[PDB]
Image 1 (cartoon, rainbow, N blue to C red):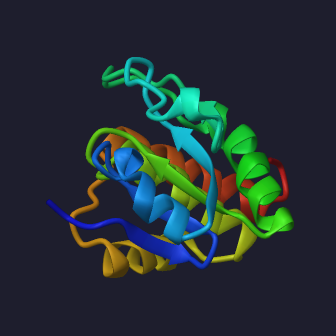
Image 2 (image 1 turned 30 degrees about the vertical axis):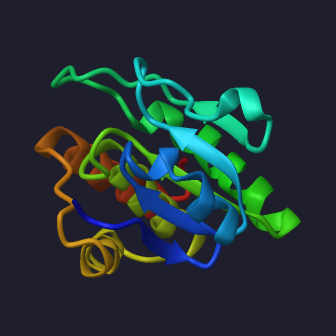
Length: 149
């Protein structure tokens, strides 16, 4: 499988395998984990090593991910501000988690939707948000450009 993707020094995009790799997470100074599924475990929860957030998305073709953007960005920033990294993952790191990272880049590094997509896809070529999530990212871009987020 594809290896964990560093996006920024404090933001890593991964799959379910990556969230179980405790030696790597400790090596990369990860202190925060976002699990973008309703059904996966929060791996290593009982060791009390990380701070976790679940964004309980399903597999539905109508899944709304925008509703989670604010919450997910706040958690990323918490990690960011205390000098810890954050791992965000779903099952494959292809679609749900990747959408959230692109949106973060759009809001917090001012990247257009196209440039943020290409930034992530350049780092992690297997990503492929579905057309539903792409539609939401376009709407998010719109709302960012009018300041109405």
